Amino acid sequence: FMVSLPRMVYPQPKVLTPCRKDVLVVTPWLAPIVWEGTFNIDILNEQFRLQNTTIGLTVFAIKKYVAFLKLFLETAEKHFMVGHRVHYYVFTDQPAAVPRVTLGTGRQLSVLEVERRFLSEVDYLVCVDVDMEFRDHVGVEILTPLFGTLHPSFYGSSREAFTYERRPQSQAYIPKDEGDFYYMGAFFGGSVQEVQRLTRACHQAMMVDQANGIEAVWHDESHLNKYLLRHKPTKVLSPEYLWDQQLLGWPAVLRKLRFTAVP
Ligand SMILES: CC(=O)N[C@@H]1[C@@H](O[C@@H]2O[C@H](CO)[C@H](O)[C@H](O)[C@H]2O[C@@H]2O[C@@H](C)[C@@H](O)[C@@H](O)[C@@H]2O)[C@H](O)[C@@H](CO)O[C@H]1O
Ligand SMILES: O=c1ccn([C@@H]2O[C@H](COP(=O)(O)OP(=O)(O)O)[C@@H](O)[C@H]2O)c(=O)[nH]1
Ligand SMILES: [Cl-]
Ligand SMILES: [Hg+2]
Ligand SMILES: [Hg+2]
Ligand SMILES: [Hg+2]
Ligand SMILES: [Hg+2]
Ligand SMILES: [Hg+2]
Ligand SMILES: [Hg+2]
Ligand SMILES: [Mn+2]
C-alpha cells in the first residue's frame, strides 16, 4: 500500500520536449537509463521516504583494500542516499582495521569478518567496489528490483567490441550477435530478493566453469553480464555512476561524475 504524495510544486514535464537528446534514456524493454536531467529527485525522495525505505550498501575490503574504507565511507556519508535509512555492510578479514567513521542519523555500519539477515534488515542491496569515492549525488533514483551500470569504457562501443566471455565452453558465454550493454561488475543492485537470485546464479555458474576447468575472461563481471542479458535489469545506470576521470576525462555527455575510481 502506497500512501498519497503531498502537494508539490515543480516544473511541468513537457511531452514535446525530450529530457536528453544526446543519449538513450530508456532501454528496448522499457527500463529507464538513469542520466542527470531525467529525474526530479524531490518526487522520488518523497516516494521512497513514504515507504521508509532502507538501503543496504555492501563492500568487500580484504588485505590492502582496507585502506580504501575511510574515503569510501566518508564520501558515502555526503552523497549516498542522504536522508534515507542506510545500513553499510563491510566484509573484511581485518575487523579492527575498519576506520572509525562518523555517521549521520539513521545510518548504521556492520562489520562482517570473512544472508537471511539482509532480507529482514534492508529493502534494497547495492553492491560496489571499495576502491572508489562518491563525488556527487547517488540516491533513490537508482532503486528498482534489479539494476546494472554501464561500464565507462564501453557505453559507446558496438557489441562485438564488448569484452564478454566468448568461449562456448563457459557458462558466461555470449556470442558476438548478442548483448545489450556491457555492465561493470563494480556497481549493481536491486531488491534483496533479486540480488540474491543474481549472486546465487553467478555462484552456481562459476562452480560449473571451475569444474570444467575454465575461468571467464573477466570473472564475476563476465557472469554478471550473462545474467543481465538473460534477466533484463529494470533500470540501467549511466556512466555517471561509475567513472574514472584520470583514464577517461570528462565528456560533455556526463553532467555529473557521481561515483569514481580512486587511483
Ligand atoms: C585501466 C585498466 O586497468 N584497464 C582498462 C579497462 O578497464 C577494465 O575493463 C575490464 C573489462 O574489459 C574490467 O571491467 C576491469 O575491471 C576494468 O578495469 C577497472 O576499471 C577501469 C575503468 C579502471 O578504473 C581500472 O583501473 C580498473 O582496474 C578498459 O575497459 C579499457 C578500455 O577503456 O582500457 C583499459 O586500460
Ligand atoms: O585484494 C583485494 C582485491 C579486491 N578486493 C575487493 O574486490 C573489489 C574488486 O577488485 P579491484 O577493485 O582490484 O578490481 P578493478 O576495479 O581493478 O577491476 C575491490 O574493490 C574490493 O572490494 C579486496 O577487498 N581485496
Ligand atoms: Cl560488489
Ligand atoms: Hg528531462
Ligand atoms: Hg551484495
Ligand atoms: Hg558486495
Ligand atoms: Hg550469472
Ligand atoms: Hg560469483
Ligand atoms: Hg555475478
Ligand atoms: Mn575496483
Image: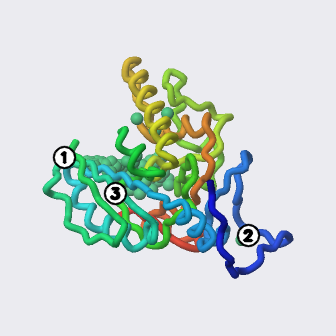
Q: Element type at marker 2? A: loop
What residue appears at the point 77 percent right and 77 percent down from the top-left corner? 12
Nearer mark to the viewer, of 1 and 3: 3
Q: Indicate whether 215 appears above or below 79.
A: above
Give, as a three-letter code, the residue at label 3: Tyr
The tag earlier along the polypeptide, 2 or 3, is 2
Q: Which residue is mark 3?
A: 88
Q: CA distance from mark 2 to mark 3?
A: 33 Å
Please give left or right for residue 26 compared with residue 52 in the image.
right
Of residues 113 and 258, which is closer to you in this image?
113
Provide residue 29's location: percent of width, then percent of height. 72, 45
Nearer mark to the viewer, of 2 and 3: 3
- Numbered label attached to residue 19: 2
The tag earlier along the polypeptide, 2 or 1, is 2
**Callout 2: CB less than 8 Å from ligand 4:** yes
Which of the 4 image quarters holds residue 259? Answer: bottom left
Q: Element type at marker 3? A: strand
Q: CA distance from mark 2 to mark 1?
A: 45 Å
Give, as a three-letter code, the residue at label 1: Asp
Give, as a three-letter code, the residue at label 2: Cys
Please give left or right for residue 61 compared with residue 225 in the image.
left
Q: Indicate whether 84 appears above or below 63.
A: below
Q: Element type at marker 1? A: loop
Q: Indicate whether 124 appears above or below 141.
A: above
Q: Which residue is mark 1?
A: 93
Q: Residue furthest right?
A: 16
Please give left or right for residue 196 compared with residue 6 in the image.
left
Of residues 93 and 2, which is closer to you in this image?
2
- Numbered label attached to residue 146: none
Provide residue 244's location: percent of width, then percent of height. 45, 63
What residue appears at the point 27 percent right and 61 percent down from the top-left corner? 68
Q: Residue furthest top?
A: 212
